[PDB]
Image (spheres, coloured by chain):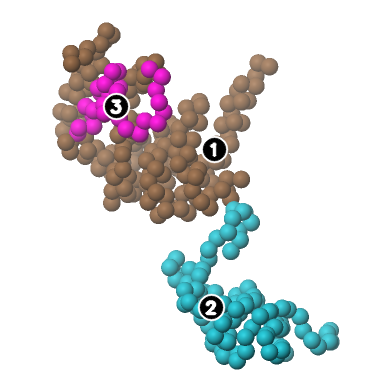
Amino acid sequence: AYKPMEGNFEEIARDFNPNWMSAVEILDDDNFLGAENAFNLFVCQKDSAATTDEERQHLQEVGLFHLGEFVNVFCHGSLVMQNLPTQGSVLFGTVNGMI
Amino acid sequence: MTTVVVHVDSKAELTTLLEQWEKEHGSGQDMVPILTRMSQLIEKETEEYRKGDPDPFDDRHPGRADPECMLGHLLRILFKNDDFMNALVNAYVMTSREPPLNTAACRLLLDIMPGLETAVVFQEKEGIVENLFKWAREADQPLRTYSTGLLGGAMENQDIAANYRDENSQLVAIVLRRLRELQLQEVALRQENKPAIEQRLILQYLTPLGEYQELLPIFM
């Protein structure tokens, strides 16, 4: 976190499971997308039940996926025209040219 | 040895108080203009202490440090209490509601301000902390004159300020508004021809929690 009143950073939470990162991207400031060297995808969701202080500094891995491809990049923006369904869009860069 | 004074003796005045309070076992007396000595016997003793040019980094007692003046002689006498003076903390705090009944604790815990080392405020009788949240939001003006720096020993502990890193922040919102008032009071009393002892003893309380985290927001 970054508290503008204090001026300094603040550790809300931290995941502990040791995965070698490859690229990460924020979805919606609640769900956080992460890649891996092991050619995989997962999202850590910020924990809701703030019953104590130990259980609110621990993120929770919510959802797993094997994207069978290395991940380099993430970015926003879509490829279709704006006609003004689903919400948001994240494109990702790879090593085999598979967007 | 044979350390007597050239003025009127202070220990004989102390022992004259040690023959009145030490024999007070349920006798039905109120020593509130007599125990004024216990807050006045040390202030004249402080008034002569400024001659020796003291080092302010004196967390210990002069009975261990400076046997040259009468400060180290007299603080050792009232500190070797042998579970006799030590029941006064259980007495004038736990069952204390009245202002002459709270006179006999707040004018006296400030007399053992170097003596209050670690574990009296750290004891499981810790409602005195929540009593001082009650004795600052709702107290009397001669009481709040002698009530702000009483948790000064609590903020010296890093364990009380971590157990109460948001309960104290409630109280900081009170004491800064009063702290703003004294610049509006005393300067306007001095802006006439063109009181600060609470201002001394509130900053004594507010100093050791001036360093801690997450308190700078309501500071600025």
As drawn, the label of residue B65 is 3
> Which lettered chain is shown in brown?
B
- Which sits earlier in the primary sequence, circle 3 or circle 1? 3
For the residue carrying disc 3, how many other residues have a C-alpha within 10 Å: few (<14), some (14-19), or many (20+)? few
Q: Which segment did they paint magenta?
A: B52-81
Residue at left offset 30%, top offset 30%: B61
Q: Residue A95: where, in percent of width, then height?
A: 67, 86
Q: Colour of chain A?
A: cyan
As drawn, the label of residue A20 is 2
Q: Name the residue under label 1.
A: B178
Q: Distance between the residues labelled 3 and 1?
A: 37 Å
**Magenta segment includes B55:** yes
Residue at left offset 64%, top offset 83%: A71
Q: Residue B199: where, in percent of width, then height?
A: 50, 31
- Majority secondary structure of magenta residues: loop
* Foreground disc of the pair 3, 1: 3
Is B206 on the left-hand or right-hand side of A42?
left
| Image-quadrant location for residue B42 | top left
Chain letter, disc 3 residue? B
